[PDB]
């Protein structure tokens, strides 16, 4: 659906080539060996364009390769090895459609994590930051051409980037208990990765009693799931949810009937029987399955804003490794993670991400005539024609439609709320009713540049588009192959320092404020309180300023849809 131009596909190909050379220039001859529970790993010292250095261990397995009869199943612990495992190169990413070339890439053998640090033997054990990548549960990787640790390793932390199964391979779900495919395999991968980290971070200079998990978009929903599930109780100590959480409408789906659909797409002939469907899918070539996934959702499902066919789901029966036994809103009520310091935030124009989609499908803007398609599914009737549904839609329309007829920008603004701000609000309010009183801080990422970018901008055809879109903040956390060395006085460089600085500060203390961070001098960053009528956030632009969340007025209008159904809010 996001279709990259020929011109950009070519610029990408040359960038990939140029990056092979840069990566070579930045690899040193110093290798090093570290211990793990499962055996020795050999890493390599790497340099950055800022002339910093760090130790790099990639391709550390945290589970058995989920191949053969392990396909679709929960991850199994990895087998120990004698000798030295080479971790001087990255492994394959999870099978997925390449977000730029449109071809399938990756491998089923993808359950790896990577560990980075500027010092393997620090005087004191360091905060460990664990990044879970986004990508709608269908794309993404921990490759350094996408998520390089180059900025974070300026700081005295251990940074770990994990992979997890994506798409149908990670999120197939079948009702039949005998089959042992309850769903959420990809989240169970994350759980098993977190367990490896808890039990191994000390070997890399990390403090197992100060672990922070963070992620953006699907990675933020993942981080939230990791804070909700009983499987991980007490495993880590801070969470950061960047542009997403588990109660976002895109973050979960009841996809139990879609395995049959995928099989039928792939040529299955027979009855809709879980067992027969599974055995067909078990023998299919993985790339074939992943290639067809885009065709799974029905017209009605897409109209109703179901975004992905396979994703996190409520597991239909309980198993020892069950991650999601109930709907996430119900899980919030009991979540161990409600009681750890938490930071959440969004960009200042999230929905700008949809620019190119509106270009391809301009009729989409007509949905704002009544806005019924954006009424939360729990409240809307099946056909979205009921008088109450039109009334709800009218509330949304008044919040976002500027003039007599809706515009593209109106649609994109509405999207920021539907997909991000409203679920953030619902989460905060729900959590406030079930927490030990531990602090939540909000940020709003509001720094716009075209001088330094990341690959999502190419994926969304957002080159030269002004405004701070979904994903734009990643540029200031992670090196990627489109980046370049910025002057220390550049606003971009300062923003990298600020973002990695605040994240590291929060990781260390559970409080994101520090007067040691340039620009944070007249800043008093207080956490949100249950009694607060209006949220305050740290707005991050060229300056750091505490403000009332500008989106609050609209958020309350969305909330008003639930006036006669408060139990569902």
Image (cartoon, rainbow, N blue to C red):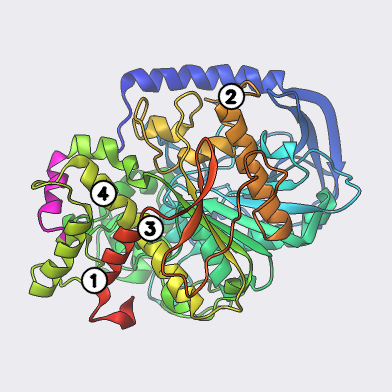
Magenta residues, start to end? 362-371
Q: Give the alpha-carbon distance from disc 1 to disc 2, as whole Å.
A: 45 Å
Q: Which residue is mark 1?
A: 561
Q: Is residue 38 visible?
A: no
Q: Is residue 216 magenta?
A: no
Q: Which residue is mark 4?
A: 295
Residue 64, percent from left and from top? 64, 56
In-image side of 398 versus 180 (left or right): left
Q: Which residue is mark 3?
A: 421
Of callouts 3 and 1, which one flags the residue occurring earlier in the amino acid sequence? 3
Is disc 2 placed on a helix, strand or loop? loop
> Residue placed at 89% from the left, 45% from the top?
121
Q: Which residue is mark 2?
A: 490
Q: Is disc 3 surrounded by few (<14), some (14 to 19) or many (20+) residues within 10 Å?
A: many
Is disc 3 placed on a helix, strand or loop? helix
Residue 517, percent from left and from top? 68, 42
> Residue placed at 40% from the left, 36% from the top?
99
């Amino acid at each position: 659906n996001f279709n990259v131009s020929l011109m950009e596909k070519l610029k990408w190909k040359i960038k990939c080539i140029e990056n092979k050379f840069l990566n070579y220039r930045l690899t040193t001859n110093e290798t090093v060996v570290a211990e793990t529970e499962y055996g020795k790993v050999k890493g390599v010292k790497r340099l950055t364009v800022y002339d910093d250095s760090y130790y790099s261990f990639e391709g550390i397995p945290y589970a058995q390769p989920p191949v053969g009869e392990l396909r679709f199943k929960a991850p199994q612990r990895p087998t120990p090895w004698d000798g030295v495992r080479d971790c001087c190169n990255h492994k394959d990413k999870s099978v997925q459609v390449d977000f730029i070339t449109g071809k399938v890439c990756g491998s089923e053998d993808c359950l790896y994590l990577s560990v980075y640090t500027n010092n393997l033997n620090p005087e004191t054990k360091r905060p460990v930051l664990v990044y879970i990548h986004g990508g709608g549960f269908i794309i993404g990787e921990n490759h350094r051409d996408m998520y390089g640790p180059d900025y974070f390793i300026k700081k005295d932390v251990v940074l770990i980037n994990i992979q997890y199964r994506l798409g149908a391979l990670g999120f197939l779900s079948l009702n039949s208990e005998d089959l042992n495919v309850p769903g959420n395999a990809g989240l169970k991968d994350q759980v098993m990765a977190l367990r490896w980290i808890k039990n191994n971070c000390a070997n890399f200079g990390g403090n197992p009693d100060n672990i922070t998990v963070f992620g953006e978009s699907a990675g933020a929903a993942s981080t939230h799931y990791m804070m909700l599930t009983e499987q991980t109780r007490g495993l880590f100590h801070r969470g950061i949810l960047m542009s997403g959480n588990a109660i976002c409408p895109w973050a979960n789906t009841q996809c139990q009937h879609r395995a049959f659909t995928l099989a039928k797409l792939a040529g299955y002939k027979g009855e809709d029987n879980d067992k027969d469907v599974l055995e067909f899918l078990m023998k299919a070539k993985p790339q074939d399955l992943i290639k067809l996934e885009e065709k799974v959702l029905t017209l009605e499902e897409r109209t109703n804003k179901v975004m992905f066919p396979f994703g996190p789901t409520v597991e239909p029966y309980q198993t020892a490794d069950c991650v999601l036994p109930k709907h996430p809103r119900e899980m919030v009520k009991t979540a161990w993670g409600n009681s750890i310091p938490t930071m959440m935030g969004n960009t200042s124009y999230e929905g700008l991400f949809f620019t190119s989609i509106l270009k391809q499908m301009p009729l989409l803007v007509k949905e704002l005539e009544t806005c019924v398609n954006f009424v939360p599914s729990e409240l809307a009737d099946a056909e979205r024609t009921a008088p109450e549904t039109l009334e709800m839609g009218a509330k949304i329309k008044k919040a976002h439609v500027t003039g007599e007829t809706p515009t593209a920008d109106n649609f994109m603004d509405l999207c920021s709320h539907f997909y991000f701000w409203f679920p953030m609000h619902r989460l905060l309010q729900l959590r406030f009713n079930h927490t030990s009183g531990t602090p939540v801080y909000l940020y709003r990422f509001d720094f716009d540049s075209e001088d330094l970018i990341n690959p999502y901008r190419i994926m969304r055809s957002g080159r030269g588009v002004k405004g701070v879109s979904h994903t734009d903040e990643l540029t200031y956390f992670f090196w990627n192959q489109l980046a370049k060395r910025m002057p220390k006085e550049s606003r971009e460089y300062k923003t990298i320092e600020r973002m990695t600085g605040i994240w590291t500060q929060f990781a260390t203390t559970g409080n994101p404020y520090s007067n040691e961070i340039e620009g944070m001098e007249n800043v008093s960053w207080d956490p949100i309180e249950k009694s607060d009528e209006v949220y305050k956030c740290l707005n991050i632009s060229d300056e750091l300023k505490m403000i009332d969340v500008p989106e609050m007025g609209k958020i309350k209008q969305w909330e008003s849809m639930f006036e006669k159904h408060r139990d569902l809010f």
